[PDB]
Image (spheres, coloured by chain):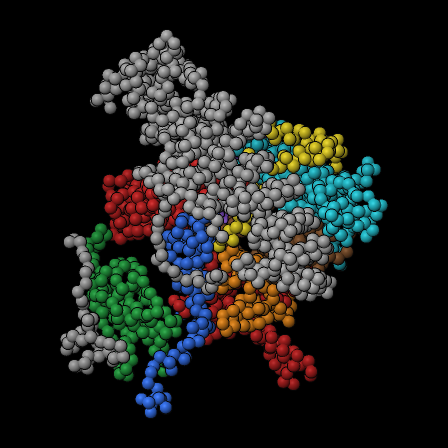
Chain colours: A purple, B cyan, E yellow, F red, G brown, H orange, J green, K blue
Amino acid sequence: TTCQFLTKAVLDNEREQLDSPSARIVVGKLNNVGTGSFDVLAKVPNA
Amino acid sequence: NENRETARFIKKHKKQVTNPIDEKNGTSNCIVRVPIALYVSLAPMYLENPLQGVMKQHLNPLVMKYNNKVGGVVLGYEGLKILDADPLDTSEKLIKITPDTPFGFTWCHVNLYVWQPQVGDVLEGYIFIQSASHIGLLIHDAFNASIKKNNIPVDWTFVHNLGHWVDSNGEPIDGKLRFTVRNVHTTGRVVSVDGTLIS
Amino acid sequence: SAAMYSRFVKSALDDLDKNDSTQIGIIANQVALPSKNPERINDKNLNILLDILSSNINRIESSRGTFLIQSIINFEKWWELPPHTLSKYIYFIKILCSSIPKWWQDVSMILVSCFILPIKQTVCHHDMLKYFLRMIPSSMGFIDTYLAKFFPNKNDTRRKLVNYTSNLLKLRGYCSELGFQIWSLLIEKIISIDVELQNELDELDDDVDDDDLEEVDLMDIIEGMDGTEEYNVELTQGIKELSTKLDSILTLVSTHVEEQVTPESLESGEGVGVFNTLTTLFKTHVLPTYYTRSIQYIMFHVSQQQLELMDSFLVTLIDISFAVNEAAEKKIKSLQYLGSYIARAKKLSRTQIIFVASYLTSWLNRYVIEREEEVDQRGGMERFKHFYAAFQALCYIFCFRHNIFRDTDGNWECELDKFFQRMVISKFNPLKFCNENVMLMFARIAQQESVAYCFSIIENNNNERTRQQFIDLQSYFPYDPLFLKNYKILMKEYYIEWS
Amino acid sequence: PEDFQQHEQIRRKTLKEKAIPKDQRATTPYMTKYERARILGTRALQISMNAPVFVDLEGETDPLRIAMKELAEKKIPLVIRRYLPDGSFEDWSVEELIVD
Amino acid sequence: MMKGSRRTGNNTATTLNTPVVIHATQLPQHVSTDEVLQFLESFIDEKENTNLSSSISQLKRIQRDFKGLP
Amino acid sequence: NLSRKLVKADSFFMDVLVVPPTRFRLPSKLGEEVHENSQNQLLSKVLTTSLLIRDLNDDLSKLRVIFSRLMNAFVTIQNDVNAFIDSTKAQSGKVPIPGVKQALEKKEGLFRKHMMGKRVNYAARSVISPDPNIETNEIGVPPVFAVKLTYPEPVTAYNIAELRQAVINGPDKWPGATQIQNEDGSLVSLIGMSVEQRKALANQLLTPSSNVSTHTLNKKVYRHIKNRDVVLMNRQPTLHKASMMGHKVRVLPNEKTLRLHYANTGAYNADFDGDEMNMHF
Amino acid sequence: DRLLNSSDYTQASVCRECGSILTTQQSVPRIGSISTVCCRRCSMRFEDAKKGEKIFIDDSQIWEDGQGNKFVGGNETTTVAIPFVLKYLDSELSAMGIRLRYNVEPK
Amino acid sequence: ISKPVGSEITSVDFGILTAKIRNLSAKQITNPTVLDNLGHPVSGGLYDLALGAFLRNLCSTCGLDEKFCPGHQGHIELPVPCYNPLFFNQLYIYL
Amino acid sequence: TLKYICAECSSKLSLSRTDAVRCKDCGHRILLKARTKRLVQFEAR
Amino acid sequence: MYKTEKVDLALNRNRGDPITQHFGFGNDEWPKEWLEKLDEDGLPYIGTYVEEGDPICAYFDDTLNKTKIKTYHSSEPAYIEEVNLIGDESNKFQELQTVSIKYRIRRTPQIGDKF
Amino acid sequence: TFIRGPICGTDNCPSRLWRIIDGRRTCQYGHVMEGDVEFNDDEDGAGVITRRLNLTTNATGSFQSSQLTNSQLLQQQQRQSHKKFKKLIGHEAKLL
């Protein structure tokens, strides 16, 4: 019932926070269940 | 009801600092230091000397070119400072790797010495050549000016043999000329300065 | 006629204020006809159109004024005009782009694209080009994008290829601030033709005399043809072109760099800048090229002219080959390059020969304590590939330069007749693990110089005997004899034969 | 103008109220099976783009097998940021985590 | 097509070339002529102790402009 | 509400449509027979009716029957935009024209067929075959599959010895390559070449290009699938996560089928009588 | 990898002011310039030059299209990596009178 | 992997297109003809060349070709405001 | 001389342009193509 | 494995429509290298080995002034077994427009066949 | 194999084009241009849409083939021209 929920999302004027995995695959964002559940940061020596 | 929208456009284009006419030379001031914040990409080959990596990838392509966000010609830079992603200062900072690529993005502060002239400014550059259509000038030995024929007083002629330009008082004009700055152009990668001698 | 067409072009010029722009699409069309269509404008009316447009500039600054300045740019064969129109055409562009500093985006699109043509064909092209370097300082940037883009195709004739690099070695001496973007554009675009040659090297090129062929030699075909034009393959690539392209181009590199090195420019000029812009281009470009002859002769041709240019490169070549902060397969290749540069170079000093070998035997005698009982531990003989590569370079010197190390008495410098006595019977056995052929001839010469007696240990490999990229670097001698038929004539003074 | 500086100041102060300090973090001291696959993923993805390697690679051509050797000797210069589900985070380095 | 790829090869302003965003964080604050030559002498000495060669020689014209004569 | 914009009534009413770009409205085709699009068919009926209700408004502008066709034209200008968005909420021969709403709601449509269920490059499928002479964590790749599937391997100082040999072998001999990527982004296919060009191009891999925009990037040789790569291997009803496991690659000559150990037949729940498995690389 | 990096994966352009994908455009450059990417509903046509004593435009905010116009503004666009179906989805919801505003946080 | 992405989409707002679509696309479509005889895209039709390049013609909006143009939108000026069948069930409450 | 074969009466029969595609002895329509002397090659496998 | 394929050129017409496309080759042009698979009547030699892509019959339509071929498009190579020539039924003067070719795919017991 | 199209980039190859493994067109010297993606559709009745056909999408890509009456200009006049013996022989018949 896709456009049932679509009209509901517009009449609510909803912001999609993009954190369910079915919403990250739609917008192409990386899923965060497993290896996407953290961030890797590189340590650089110079100030 | 026609003011809450039109106000959003005037302050978008109103320049922050106007150029002042300084030390009573007539010449206005156009060299200005501005602090900026960047969002750049450090690369894996420069992961041992990160300051040299940002300087060689993002800062050196920017010098001596017109930049949109500062409204001027970026002369040089001073004081690069990478923002740490760890709000603990220190040398061993750390930046964030993108998930897909090995590239790391970060924030940086640096002071840009930019050259920002506006309209209504007065500059003194040396005349490169002169003809019976224009006067061409090297502003500060690096920039270019073009005083067109409608922007020259009518009582100033041109003697020909090429040749010197003739003013009203019969003086063949010398290189170091004062001129009023008209609409500064953007169009080519060569960034020129239109001018007037009329007032 | 001359007074008739002078107001014919002012009526069209006054059509900006009349606001219809009548003959701008006609008068400037007339100057846009090609040379092969003789219905174009003559030069007398071209003086008429020019001096109207050189003396009034206010009335072209519009999008209707675009097409006429386009036509002066696209004026084909402007460099073949008579001097009362040529020297007036030159003065147009010098005040066109002065009045509007926008068209220089598009003028040197035409000026750099005519560097294909020869030197005396385009002596006026550099007169306008150098002018706008001292005129427009912020044009050094995008000129470099015009040199790389209008560098010719690799499979062109040499006429587009020996006259482009000639016009581009022309560009260096007038602007050394450009400098590094010239040689990087040459050296990488020489390897494009260079390494397409040695993988052919099976049989010789016949010296056919028809090398320098001809003098100066001097239709729309625009249809809807984008269907199938199948099976017109004829896949053939020439070979004797490619030995003569490197004859043509790389002689002119070494003939003009012969102008660029002489001590009048090495002491008060920019000749050391030539020497530094190639050695820093040596270790970046040509040293990671696998199996490439005939391009390391340029650094060989230059670093032999003075005693300084030699000695300011031997210390550079060794710092590549013995610093820990490099890659190992660079370090082995520079040792591979060092023994072949010393022994295959004619005009050197004899005290330059010994200091390489004195430092090299020092490195083996600074090896003498630290790493000479590591062999018996659990590992391989591949842990010592830097040591074997350095000893192999030592053997390659003595197989060529041996009589230098004989002193006046008849003895050997720095105990070379005692040094190999220790190295052979050491617990590395460098007779087996170095190259076979450089060690085969070293055993013969050690008998004919009475230095070592290492026949029976090369004999002592009967039942006794990753590695493939280490055997192969022992087979790449950098100063193998040149195949190029016409560049060796210059190299005959510099490069030593077999005997 | 200053309206950027009013926003950068907020963004970094909000990012200061999420950084849990090194004395107060309360997650596990183990490398939890997914760091190890992503550390060796990302470090090998750097070594293939000419990163400086801090191990004596001995004829190993595989970039992933090199990172598995930089991990065993604690030579990987990376930092894991463990997100707690309100947004706040703990920065654990790779040297102090314990690999399985 | 070809000249579609020339215009991709014309600019080539990507995220290794150019930064993502640039914001001016304060008001631009002018300096005297006495601090321009104080700056251009140290900045040229830093970058000459590759590319940037087409840029520094324009600064040396600018450096010579505040005290000398073409 | 942080913009404090007003909830207005013209949110409910459509003063204009928008038309999708031409790329999204290309003509349909069957064989040589290139028909007209579904989307243009509905969108023209609105545009004829809009011109009518404009032309007939000029007819009533000079003063009955003309008031009864204008009011009937409001029924059908509403009914044809109702047809443009929905299909069941319009009238239809037997099965009417699909609207943009009904292009979205089933197993097919858009939101499950092309957003959760995309089709992928670098994949292969074949019948599987038993093998006790491979490792249990392995799949036996045929040489038919092996000379097609390629992996971009960036050329560096530690792999130029094995990537020169890949460009020399070319896309016929197995431990080879198919195309190399320059530092500018363009590719160079090695298919039609001979050993002259390929050996003269393997020797240029570590050469820096003169550009400064791409002085960071290096080249990428698209080597074939060697014995050290891995593979996602996929029995087709994936009822649990052990039906999609990661095998190592062992390239076997002289075979036409994927070839799998017996220890993996309980995990995928496979019986070796014609099961196809997807090989994702 | 098996749902973006192999299937479609476009690097599209996105305006950082209206937050929309399909309102972007690379300009037709005037003959000296290089073409750049500029939004459309964040843009204002050059006829709207209505009233620092004067409010003249910096000429770097002025871009053209091939149909003739000059627009002011429309800058602040970026490049994000999306699937292509999101570009097609956002062109089907526009036909329904529905807009999708994308929040792109590095600003 | 050698083309990194910086900015990235973090959250998605839903919304309604106001009738100021005339800002982003005034290339409006009035002719219900799709193609003429002799196969050309007619001006002001549903295959106009300002809506993106088509049949090897250039885009009148991009200046780019058949492949490189992203496509562009176009509006159809309804002379009267007929309502939307999506939001109709939820204005019939409010009426 | 290329020919054909009538499928019914088995008469060998060449056929030219502007001819009814028929046999000329019986009136049969189905008219199969004969094979001529022409080299094909095989592995003996 | 045998397999037939009806090659019909009268699919595109009505009964009141005159003839457009004709079997056999065209002149005033060079259709290259199609004569190794095909005979001078536009039909294949029988016994001929055809792969995917290979021409299977030549026709000449008058509405293009051009000789196009039809193509054997199948994953499995075959041999032309039979070529039949279907005559007309209605009138006694029009050209042949229906040809049914028979292919022969050899099928040795490869690995994966079920016994 | 080769399909002649435009000239090619790189300042190297001026030649025709040629498609590569299933998806993209290259020159014969190795160089390949961007955006070359072949746009082939799927196959699934399928809506009551069977009319208004003018194109035939030849040349391995998008569209623009079969222009209407681009060779019919001699076609309706070659029924009355190709065949002989029209019995219009009036004064030549007395010579015949």
Q: Residue furthest top?
A: C409
| Extreme residue toward the right, this view | B169
Residue F34: give x, y in percent of width and height.
43, 68
> Please, is residue F215 above or below residue H31 in the view?
above
- In the rendered picture of this protein, how many numbered marks are placed on residues? 0
Q: Is residue D29 visible?
A: no
> A1 or B22, which lies in front?
B22
In the foreground, C472 or F4: C472
Residue J69 location, quadrant: bottom left
Residue C253 % position (x, y) = 48, 35
Q: Is residue B126 above or below residue C66?
A: above
Q: Residue at x 60, y 29 (%)?
A: E48
Task: Establish if K19 lies above or below B86.
Answer: below
Horizontal placement of I7 versus C278: left or right? left
In the picture provided, is E17 more to the left or to the right than F58?
left
Residue B166, visible in the rendered structure: yes
Query: Residue F66 vs residue K42: left or right?
Result: right
Of residues C482 and D66, which is closer to you in this image? C482
Q: Residue at x 71, y 57 (%)?
A: C59
Q: Position of residue B128 (x, y in %)?
A: 71, 42
Name the residue located 50 percent from the left edge and 40 percent from the top edge: C165
Q: Position of residue F95 (x, y in %)?
A: 45, 72
Q: Residue at x 60, y 75 (%)?
A: F51
Compared with residue C287, is residue J74 higher up or lower down, i.e. above or below?
below
Which quadrant of the view contains residue F246?
top left
